[PDB]
Amino acid sequence: KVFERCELSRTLKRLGMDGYRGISLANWMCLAKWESGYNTRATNYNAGDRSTDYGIFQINSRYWCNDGKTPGAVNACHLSCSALLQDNIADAVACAKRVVRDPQGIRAWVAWRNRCQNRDVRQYVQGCGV
Image (cartoon, rainbow, N blue to C red; front, side):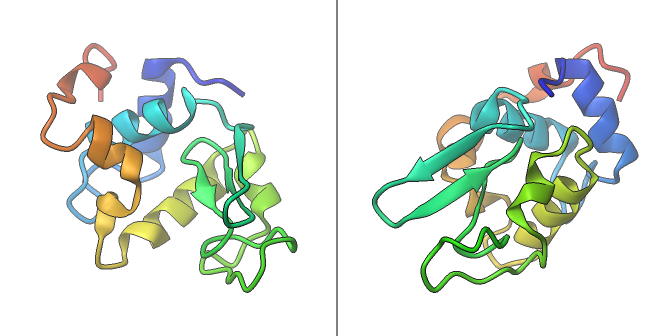
C-alpha cells in the first residue's frame, strides 16, 4: 500500500509513534517519506552485504527481521521480514520502535541523517490534524 501523507501521520499517531523515545511524528514522517515514499511493499537488496531492506521504513534484515537468506543475520524484532511488507503497518511500527530503543535512536537510518536531521520537518505533518 502507498499511504497518502496525512493518512499516514494519523496512522502513526494512533500507533503511538508521536514522541516515542523523544522522536516527533514529523521525524517519522520524514523518515518514511525518504525511505520508501510511504510504500509498505518497498524492498531494496544490498548486493554488497547480501541483506535486504523491507517496508515503509526499509528495515534491514541483517539485524532486525528474519528472511532466512542473510548470512550471520539476527532478528532483533523477532519477526519474519514478510511482516514488514503488510498494508497494515502495526508490525513495522513495533519494529521501528525496537530500532530506536538502541543507542543511536532515529539516527539508525542514514537517510534520516541525510534528509531529516537539522531540517525543517514541520511540513511533513502540516494540515494533517495530528
